[PDB]
Length: 49
Length: 50
Image (cartoon, rainbow over all chains, first blue to last red; front, side):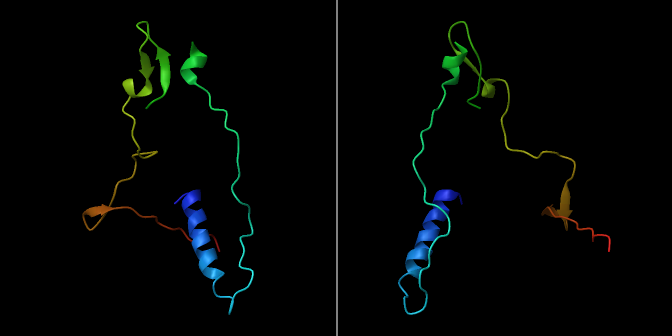
């Protein structure tokens, strides 16, 4: 499935989870949220030349 | 496929797809299996010593 799709799934379940406060409190993700990152992509051709 | 091997005199590019079929395929083509004459795969298991 891949990260994105899982991240959705997770949220689905996590959203659907947090609407039953009757039975289930603090249903949280234990890991980290996606973040921005600076990608320095190289042109191959260019370097050759 | 879009890999760049060299750039040509007329300026065109030599892509990997130019000098190779590029396909998804088995690391090896040693084993071919068949369940009842039909296309199959499997894994045989060998119980660990003890």
